[PDB]
Image 1: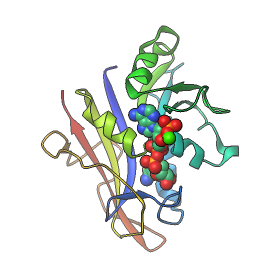
Image 2 (image 1 turned 90 degrees about the vertical axis):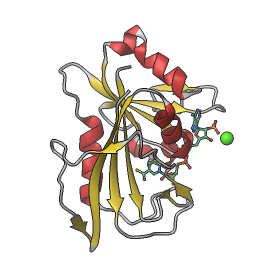
Image 3 (image 1 turned 45 degrees about the vertical axis):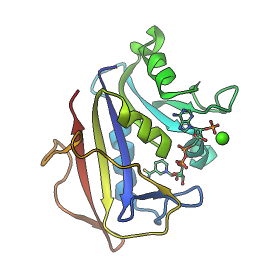
Length: 186
Ligand SMILES: NC(=S)c1ccc[n+]([C@@H]2O[C@H](COP(=O)([O-])OP(=O)(O)OC[C@H]3O[C@@H](n4cnc5c(N)ncnc54)[C@H](OP(=O)(O)O)[C@@H]3O)[C@@H](O)[C@H]2O)c1
Ligand SMILES: [Ca+2]
């Protein structure tokens, strides 16, 4: 596949989760952002693919599965078949990657989005492939039990601007955050 996209929201301590959920209470605007980014395809008749870990899939309220308008791929070394509502189950990122290149998929899919968790982000980041990382930096700390892996600042260059990503500091529910896009060129 040409390139990857990963999207995550992180707080000051690099936490991305707590007790099987997000560390902060709901932020509407950030959510819409996530939906818009992962769902929008730039080609008619095609859809985006989202890849996620087992825990992440299960963190989504059952009635909200799978993420509508995207091909949901869940990774697990343990499951024997895709969880109810998921489109495909893969045993590794590589497997998922191969799957995508498969004929059936290849023609059906526009963009690939990595939606976490930890181990998933890490694996995608290590692939020597063109990758864009969309980060929402929440400028506050919340107790977290799950964290974003460390990004190689030598590989991933922070863009100073990106089409359709606001530059300013955003605020909502008395909380501030900023969007940042990092890019790795292979
Ligand atoms: N802040 C944002 S945007 C965000 C995004 C995602 C998740 N989260 C949060 O983080 C937590 C879930 O993340 P996590 O890190 O704990 O768990 P996940 O990555 O979602 O799930 C871990 C499981 O997933 C499977 N897995 C993970 N990486 C794999 C790989 N490379 N190949 C095969 N299977 C792989 C394994 O399943 P098996 O054990 O069955 O093999 C592993 O036990 C929740 O709190 C969730 O809310 C936050
Ligand atoms: Ca396990």
